[PDB]
Image 1 (cartoon, helix red, strand yellow):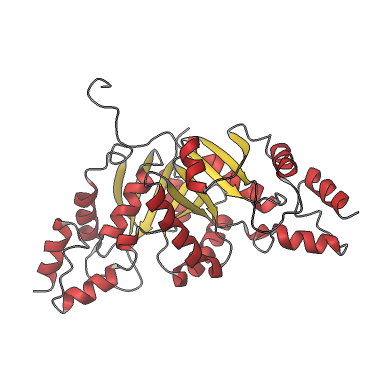
Image 2 (cartoon, one colour; image 1 turned 180 degrees about the horizontal axis):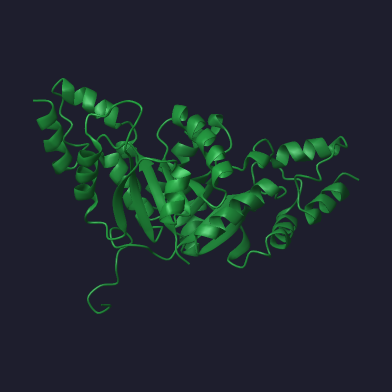
Length: 173
Length: 159
């Protein structure tokens, strides 16, 4: 019915979905891989968006981050990896995304997540935020904590894909 | 291919908050069932029949949504319905903790079922069924928070 209407996204059934999953991914962990695997199972396309210039100086640069993720996520056909240096809503808009994946680890974060969701609704109304709990197995891990365990020689082989574990050991002499 | 999501709840009764959640879910998944708990441990104002009838009318305009009672383990219901997603609205910090527990249990009971969480719109971020009832019970104006059909049925219950 194209000559009458192009269509609306609401009240008219299911629509093509394209999700961004933004983060610093410094580096990508198995907790991250789990989230995006889950989101890629239920949305048509997912983009792992890696922040170029995070406020705190990352251990891996963008080019390293992007490469490690690419490799770690290549077995998922509907996932692509991109760096970005914008608001997550502007990137979403540029990418013609309509879904924003957010991992939801801690109670302490829930307020902030809600507030950021409200900001994003104001910024890009047609962008929907969707929240995924982490697996029980990855509930206590973070990039930051894996890096600090690793610096002081703790075993983190369980928490990382192999390519990342190797890059990480190299960073730490 | 197909996504089919369950949105379970007591829905005693369905509010504008719930309607926002399911409108949003039904825009992202091919089909959505509103799943209404038959026998909540606290006895509801509206019985299952009424809760279902109300919710059906409020959601009639959504072509890929269907309202159903259920009185079994949600794992079994999702499995009976060939659902592969579970939708939860997430209003409060208090409710996050509990839903994260139920989610881990659901992962044990049904690995293939993915739990998914939406935040309420700002508009509806403070309303619950319980609160609308409380306010209405002492004659407060709650017309902004319910669809007409539910509004009239609530007024009737309180008279």
